[PDB]
Image (cartoon, coloured by chain):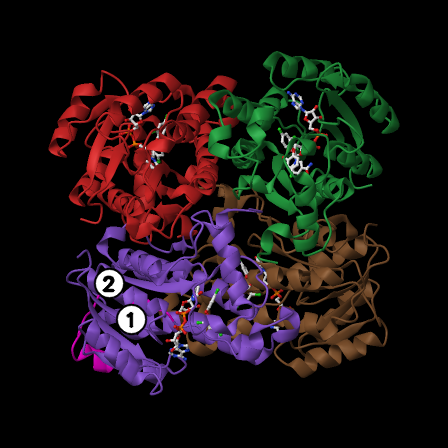
Chain colours: A red, B green, C brown, D purple
Amino acid sequence: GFLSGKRILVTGVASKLSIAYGIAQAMHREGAELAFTYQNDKLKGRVEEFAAQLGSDIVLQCDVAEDASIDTMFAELGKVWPKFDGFVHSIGFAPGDQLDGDYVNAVTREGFKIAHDISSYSFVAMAKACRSMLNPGSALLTLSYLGAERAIPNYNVMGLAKASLEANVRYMANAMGPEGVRVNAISAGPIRTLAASGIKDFRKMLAHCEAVTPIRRTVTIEDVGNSAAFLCSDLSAGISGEVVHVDGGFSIAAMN
Amino acid sequence: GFLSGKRILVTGVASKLSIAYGIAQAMHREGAELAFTYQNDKLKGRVEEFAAQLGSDIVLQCDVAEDASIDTMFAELGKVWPKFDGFVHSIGFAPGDQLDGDYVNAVTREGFKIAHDISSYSFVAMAKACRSMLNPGSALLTLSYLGAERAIPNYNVMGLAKASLEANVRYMANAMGPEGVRVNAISAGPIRTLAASGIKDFRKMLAHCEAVTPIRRTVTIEDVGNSAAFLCSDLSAGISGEVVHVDGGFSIAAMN
Amino acid sequence: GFLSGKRILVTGVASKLSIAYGIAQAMHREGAELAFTYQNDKLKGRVEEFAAQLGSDIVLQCDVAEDASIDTMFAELGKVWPKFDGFVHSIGFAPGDQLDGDYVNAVTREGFKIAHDISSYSFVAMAKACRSMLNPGSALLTLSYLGAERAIPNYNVMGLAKASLEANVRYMANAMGPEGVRVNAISAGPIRTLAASGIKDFRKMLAHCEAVTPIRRTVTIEDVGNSAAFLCSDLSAGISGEVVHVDGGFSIAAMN
Amino acid sequence: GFLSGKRILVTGVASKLSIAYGIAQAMHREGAELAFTYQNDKLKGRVEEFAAQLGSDIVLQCDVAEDASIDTMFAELGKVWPKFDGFVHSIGFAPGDQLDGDYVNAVTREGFKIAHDISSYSFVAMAKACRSMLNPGSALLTLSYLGAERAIPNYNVMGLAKASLEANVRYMANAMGPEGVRVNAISAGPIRTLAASGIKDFRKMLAHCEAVTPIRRTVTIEDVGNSAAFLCSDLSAGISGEVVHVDGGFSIAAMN
Ligand SMILES: NC(=O)c1ccc[n+]([C@@H]2O[C@H](COP(=O)([O-])OP(=O)(O)OC[C@H]3O[C@@H](n4cnc5c(N)ncnc54)[C@H](O)[C@@H]3O)[C@@H](O)[C@H]2O)c1
Ligand SMILES: NC(=O)c1ccc[n+]([C@@H]2O[C@H](COP(=O)([O-])OP(=O)(O)OC[C@H]3O[C@@H](n4cnc5c(N)ncnc54)[C@H](O)[C@@H]3O)[C@@H](O)[C@H]2O)c1
Ligand SMILES: NC(=O)c1ccc[n+]([C@@H]2O[C@H](COP(=O)([O-])OP(=O)(O)OC[C@H]3O[C@@H](n4cnc5c(N)ncnc54)[C@H](O)[C@@H]3O)[C@@H](O)[C@H]2O)c1
Ligand SMILES: NC(=O)c1ccc[n+]([C@@H]2O[C@H](COP(=O)([O-])OP(=O)(O)OC[C@H]3O[C@@H](n4cnc5c(N)ncnc54)[C@H](O)[C@@H]3O)[C@@H](O)[C@H]2O)c1
Ligand SMILES: Oc1cc(Cl)ccc1Oc1ccc(Cl)cc1Cl
Ligand SMILES: Oc1cc(Cl)ccc1Oc1ccc(Cl)cc1Cl
Ligand SMILES: Oc1cc(Cl)ccc1Oc1ccc(Cl)cc1Cl
Ligand SMILES: Oc1cc(Cl)ccc1Oc1ccc(Cl)cc1Cl
């Protein structure tokens, strides 16, 4: 595969519907060796089953709200992977109250704090912690959403965290590029996942996109995963700091 | 002038070089009634002097890091301006350690938290706090920098904070527009100010910019203040959720 | 007013609904001296009436499809305004066949040629033709549409023409800035005008926009003219090579 | 390869340094069947040698300035490829005089005409002519440059043609998407090619980029070709109307 000889760490696999899950499959189909992290014990065993299917016995607990957790995970990771080639950051979070109705009324200081910390900061946090274990030709990838670029109803403060994140991709890419590390983001169209269910009228959001999207269908985790495998492979060597839209063309069309 | 009948609240006047200062002067020259806030005790009397000069005797304290301070300032404001027509948010802050050398190495969880809290959240926190005192036709304004859109050396996490901020403008503009409130931002080119001194080799920025800028000069606080008065007056009724670049054209040129 | 002492040349007044008309009115309300051009004989007397009303008796013919017409208009202009302070380019055209149904099927080599020639080239052709009559502090302005940035149904090749136009603003701003000339564009939201009637289901555009627009209303020629007066006055000294959106916020929102 | 079972037509191979050449290699390495066009007889035999190496005996003359030439080529193409899966548009042109010094002085009506016609229109022209021979899952790709987004010295009118083109990708993608056709663009960093030699100080342009680019090197046709193979493969199914930057990160960095 085009990822043969690559060791990539994959975050965010909550279930078989997760973008991370679809991403690991594409990467594994492409010859990459994978390592998975699980946020907690509620998720532990599940992630272990998926690791096994993708031929990996590296499943480490990691909660990006904690520096020491990121730190410990990388330590256990180095035991098998002293040096690796990148990671996939598929982690996003905002307190439930943050996501519905008028943004100005919903947003609070803490919610803003948590949303930016978990969705934006965690990306660089993970980079700091493993920066020295990365081989040249490494690539990091995170997942963003159009709410970063446009004011989308109910997405509220998550739109700001995503905007922060995209700026992170640029700052990381400019800082880590000179040492052989690329950093990019896939701006994915809406996909029904556990987290998606936290946004009001997601079902109508999906149907809308399916209708107004040039390709005339919503994207799949297979679609996203394929772009992800590419962005983390040497095939995308000339791309860094880029936010690739994998939404079928939705954001470029208008009043369809 | 074109702001006659407008009562505007101006924040961030730390000195006669402050962008907020240059903005207050233009808004005063165009007929507006102003109210000033000062962050702390160190700045108080300085702000009172300028206020007096701009014919205002409404100088209230406000530390945007504290909700209670934001809430009290508006209660105090209500006593004189039960209803007013918008405010200028000219506040920014990132801990000193954050602003120099490699981004990834420089950034920390608290620096990120703080940079975002003071540079981005505070904007919406203020809007929430006075949402009901705003008259139809009200305009809210904030100041951003190109760091939001491009990875600029040393600007580091402040670029991420601005990215979040510009997103905020869009989400606030979308949320408040329905009740008669516009929200926009001026993306100002570099200007030597108190806070400007906190970035490495700023002197070279200013000169680099002066040379590669289409208008061939760096912008002024007079420049920025005229655009801000415009953006907080009825002259800009057709504009909302916009980040206008008052950088003399610097960002649209390349390899000049 | 803020344009007192400014002599501006206004193009594209086809009627009292014309954006150029609403612009001329604001520029006149702010103290500017205007000069008007009319495309042909059919429009001549109409333009003379408005001119007279806006206190001007300088009405010259100008078909931007002909260099010689552009050259003669300026020679005639020189006789009264040897030097002036900029002009408003409010001219757009694509053959009728170009504007409806599927883009690819609708577009032809000549329609493309024409749409670009009249909607984009003409802007720089006029600047070339008067480059030496422009005083320092001069401003050039043009009008664009969101079609440049997003694929909008039926707008077809005109969107490509606008894309070329917005690029022109940037290249002209960069080239002329050094001699004291700023060049910008207003990206106006839909407004019912003579040319507006040439697009399919425009009535539904206007209503769709009125509903999904942050300010909850479509912009007016008054709205656009105040932003244009601002952009052609010294109030916008810090702005050049910029495409300001006077669409009430429509483009920054999504799935409203 | 990931392009196995794909028949792609490749335009623009002038020499072994051509972006098209590097693109065909990547596509051929990935299992795709290719067909090549040559603009003229000066180029004919050369393109035939490259076709042979890439295992293709389909080399058709095509000059995109002529509808009948595009038309005839597709007719001869259908003889072997009744239906195919897409094409690579790597064609750009502007009269020599257009490319040096002050844009406003260099640009002329004809130069603008030719530059837009050959660099922008030809893309859709080719799409019109073959629209019905495309299988579902087809993808078209064109090559753009940052001069479309920023005013780059000496690029002059080519920057406008590229802006027109990028708008074309969006219009094409929105029109052809519903029938199973994606349209995208690679915005390539500077690469020394025959055409490149038409831009003043290209050598200094290259060195600059190599220094200020996050990856710290200029891109290669291998880099571009790899992204091209991906954008024309089912791997990029969720991407359409996108302008992917393959420039190492140059456009996202600032004042490096
Ligand atoms: N699904 C969509 O429609 C969509 C579209 C664009 C982008 N995204 C992004 O893709 C990523 C994956 O989202 P998803 O939709 O697949 O949902 P998901 O629920 O499958 O995955 C969310 C993941 O984030 C993890 N996470 C959150 N907080 C954590 C923490 N504190 N520490 C460690 N892990 C934590 C959860 O365990 C989970 O594995 C998110 O960034 C999301 O914003 C989603
Ligand atoms: N100066 C530049 O070149 C430039 C360019 C682009 C953007 N900006 C932005 O303009 C705004 C004003 O900054 P400036 O350059 O005029 O500098 P300045 O130092 O004169 O003012 C910044 C203001 O921030 C206030 N502030 C800091 N923390 C705050 C808090 N906790 N509570 C209340 N107020 C707070 C300070 O009192 C100060 O008045 C900032 O957002 C800045 O990022 C400046
Ligand atoms: N009306 C809208 O909703 C809207 C929105 C965005 C952009 N625009 C732009 O505003 C500008 C003015 O158009 P409008 O909507 O006011 O319509 P309008 O029909 O009132 O005016 C367009 C003008 O184009 C002039 N024109 C056409 N070909 C020209 C030529 N060959 N020589 C000289 N002049 C030429 C006509 O005389 C006419 O005055 C156009 O660029 C248009 O694309 C309009
Ligand atoms: N090389 C770079 O630095 C760079 C960067 C970004 C984008 N691009 C684009 O890539 C494409 C390929 O450029 P290149 O740099 O490889 O140069 P090149 O000289 O190898 O290729 C240019 C091709 O366009 C063809 N062409 C031009 N007019 C033609 C016509 N009338 N009909 C048919 N074919 C014609 C020429 O035969 C040639 O094959 C162009 O669009 C160029 O703008 C180049
Ligand atoms: O960002 C997303 C965008 C869409 Cl359309 C759907 C799901 C998304 O993902 C999230 C949304 C809200 C929270 Cl709290 C956490 C996550 Cl992971
Ligand atoms: O944002 C700015 C951009 C420039 Cl070019 C100059 C000064 C700026 O203002 C700040 C920079 C850093 C911090 Cl800590 C706080 C502020 Cl207010
Ligand atoms: O650009 C426009 C955009 C909108 Cl929404 C409405 C009218 C416009 O104006 C034009 C549209 C088509 C052609 Cl043929 C010429 C012009 Cl002047
Ligand atoms: O677009 C380009 C951009 C760069 Cl940096 C280098 C070469 C380019 O390609 C061209 C430039 C000018 C002409 Cl007339 C034709 C072509 Cl193909």
Q: Disc 2 residue type?
A: Met
Q: Are marks 2 and 1 in contact (CB under 8 Å)?
A: yes
Same-chain check, marks 2 and 1: yes
| Chain ID, mark 1 | D
Whether residue B252 is visible here, answered yes or no, is yes
Q: Secondary structure at mark 1?
A: strand
Q: Disc 1 residue type?
A: Val
**Classed neighbour count for the residue bearing mark 1: other residues with Cα under 10 Å, few (<14), some (14–19), many (≥20):** many
Q: Which residue is mark 2?
A: D27
What separation in Å lies between label 2 and label 1 (alpha carbons)? 10 Å
Above or below, comparing residue A192 to residue A177 in the picture: above
Task: Please name the residue shown 26% across and 44% down the image.
Answer: A229
Q: Quadrant of residue B45?
A: top right
From the Cβ of disc 2, is ligand 4 less than 8 Å away?
Answer: no
- Please state the horizontal and vertical placement of residue A18, each as a whole percent of the image: 24, 32
Q: Which residue is mark 1?
A: D10
From the viewer's perspective, tell me whether residue A68 is left or right of residue C235: left
Q: Secondary structure at mark 2?
A: helix
Q: Quadrant of residue C36?
A: bottom right
Mark identifier at residue B2: none
- Please state the horizontal and vertical placement of residue B195, each as a whole percent of the image: 68, 30
Answer with mark 2 or mark 1, whichever residue precedes in sequence. 1
Image: magenta residue range: D73-90
Q: Nearer the viewer, residue C70 or A120?
A: A120
Whether residue C18 is visible here, answered yes or no, is no
